Image (cartoon, grey):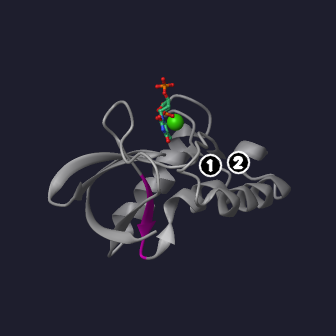
Amino acid sequence: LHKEPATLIKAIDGDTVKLMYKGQPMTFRLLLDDTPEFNEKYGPEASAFTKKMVENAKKIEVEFDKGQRTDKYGRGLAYIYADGKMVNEALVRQGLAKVAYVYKGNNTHEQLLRKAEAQAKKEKLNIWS
Ligand SMILES: Cc1cn([C@H]2C[C@H](OP(=O)(O)O)[C@@H](COP(=O)(O)O)O2)c(=O)[nH]c1=O
Ligand SMILES: [Ca+2]
């Protein structure tokens, strides 16, 4: 896979963010994550964690996987990096997202994320407390 440039337009919630990609505004949904909705437990914390990660970054990048690049709602489906750190992985490692929505072709980082989930669960972090 390859990392491509983007810039932050606005944080939205734990697993969606609005970025400018190839000069166009797009909402991205983070591959392989399911954060709780803002109105659910750990929802606000997940939104806050992603917001801090993308707002503080000097450089955002998006990385598409091998499969579909947009979902049925027109959201971009990618791995998002903030100063080289993958937000998709970080949310899982901190117990603020579950690994979810693992569809064939878009699962390059599946094993990396499941290893993070196992550690978050062992630590009884957040969702796993
Ligand atoms: C993460 C992701 C979600 N989706 C679709 C499936 C779900 O459809 P439904 O809306 O019919 O439940 C929805 C979940 O996203 P959210 O967790 O943002 O609600 O987005 C994909 O199709 N591909 C994906 O990789
Ligand atoms: Ca969600």
Q: What element does badge 2 sit on?
A: helix
**Mark 1 Cα within 10 Å, few/some/many (few <14, many 20+)?**
many
- The residue type indicated by label 1 comes to Leu
Work out whether mark 2 precedes mark 1 in sequence or the reverse, and give the earlier one: 1
Most extreme residue toward the left, as rendered? 23
The image shows residue 26, relative to residue 79, as above or below, that is above
Between 108 and 7, the one nearer to me in the picture? 108
* Distance between the alpha carbons at the discs numbered 2 and 1: 6 Å
Q: Quadrant of residue 29?
A: top left
* Residue range of the region highlighted in magenta in the rendering: 78-83
* Residue under pointer 2: 126
Residue 125 drawn at (x, y percent): 74, 53
| Residue drawn at 42 percent across, 76 percent down | 83
| Residue drawn at 19 percent across, 49 percent down | 25
Q: What element does badge 1 sit on?
A: loop
Q: Is residue 79 magenta?
A: yes
**Mark 2 Cα within 10 Å, few/some/many (few <14, many 20+)?**
some
Quadrant, the C terminus: top right
Between 97 and 80, the one nearer to me in the picture? 80
- The residue type indicated by label 2 comes to Asn
Q: Tell how many labels.
A: 2
Between 22 and 13, the one nearer to me in the picture? 22
The image shows residue 28, relative to residue 58, as above or below, that is above
Residue 17 drawn at (x, y percent): 36, 49
The label nearer to you, 2 versus 1, is: 1
Asked whether disc 2 touches disc 1, contact meaning CB atoms under 8 Å apart, the reply is: yes
Residue 4 drawn at (x, y percent): 32, 69
Prevailing SS of the magenta stretch: strand
Identify the disc placed on residue 96.
Answer: 1
Q: Is residue 2 magenta?
A: no
| Residue drawn at 54 percent across, 38 percent down | 43
